[PDB]
Image: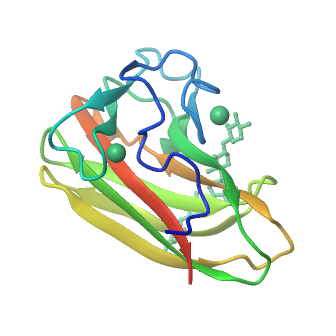
Amino acid sequence: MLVANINGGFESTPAGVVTDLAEGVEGWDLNVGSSVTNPPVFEVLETSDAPEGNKVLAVTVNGVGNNPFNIQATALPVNVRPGVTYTYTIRARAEQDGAVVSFTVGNQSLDEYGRLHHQQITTEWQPFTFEFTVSDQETVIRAPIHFGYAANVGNTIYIDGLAIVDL
Ligand SMILES: O[C@@H]1[C@@H](O)[C@H](O[C@@H]2CO[C@@H](O[C@@H]3CO[C@@H](O[C@@H]4CO[C@@H](O[C@@H]5CO[C@@H](O)[C@H](O)[C@H]5O)[C@H](O)[C@H]4O)[C@H](O)[C@H]3O)[C@H](O)[C@H]2O)OC[C@H]1O
Ligand SMILES: [Ca+2]
Ligand SMILES: [Ca+2]
């Protein structure tokens, strides 16, 4: 496969809680805003249930901030070509009913090219997919996943298998 993103399945990363948010996971930047007073737990988990490889990323939300992007996992770098249309696919599930996640892609200037907005995450693995086009002249973009929805308090959201593919 030819994918734009790096370590889309977390297989590069040792199992355990991630405390180095910026650099602890190859190909990703994790972020927690200061309005989140009970910070989430990001953990790379080795599990027989992983849809891809042996590992998944678990995001335990024990509270939230002011905006859903106050808890986020962003794939970076994402290597693309101007004008090209990509398919984004990822797998996600949650520990408990009722989770909400937005899957987004944008540039380093924070302009958003597209998203899946307030996706309904269930307790079973499901794929979430959309297309976007690089509408400007960027070659290195990013893919922010937003987890800080109030409905996720008391839940863990599991993601795996991010693939951003030409089309
Ligand atoms: O440390 C820094 C981080 O804080 C930083 O985080 C990034 C901040 O910028 C974020 O991008 C903004 C996200 O919000 C976008 O506006 C959205 C767009 O979507 C709107 O919802 C639409 C509703 O209707 C639907 O049909 C449609 O599908 C939806 O899109 C929603 O209402 C708006 O809030 C802004 O345009 C973005 O700029 C980015 O995600 C974060 O990663 O990152 C850098 C780091 O240094
Ligand atoms: Ca995996
Ligand atoms: Ca990083």
Q: In percent of the image, x 34 and y 67: which residue is there?
A: 128
Q: Hey, which residue is sitting farthest front in the picture?
A: 1
Q: Quadrant of ligand 3?
A: top right
Q: In percent of the image, x 33 and y 61: which residue is there?
A: 119
x, y percentage for residue 136?
82, 76
x, y percentage for residue 52?
30, 51
Q: Hey, which residue is sitting farthest right in the picture?
A: 137
x, y percentage for residue 101?
37, 52
Q: In percent of the image, x 31 and y 23: which residue is there?
A: 62
Q: In percent of the image, x 38 and y 43: which residue is there?
A: 149
For residue 157, which quarter of the picture? Answer: top left
Is 164 drawn above or below residue 157 in the view shown?
below
Task: Say left or right for 65 vs 47.
Answer: right
For residue 86, which quarter of the picture? Answer: bottom right
Residue situated in front as seen by the camera: 114 or 76: 76
Quadrant in the picture for the C terminus: bottom right
Task: Say left or right for 15 vs 46.
Answer: right
Task: Say left or right for 37 vs 141.
Answer: left
Residue situated in front as seen by the camera: 5 or 70: 5
Is 142 drawn above or below residue 39 in the view shown?
below
Is 34 drawn above or below residue 162 in the view shown?
above
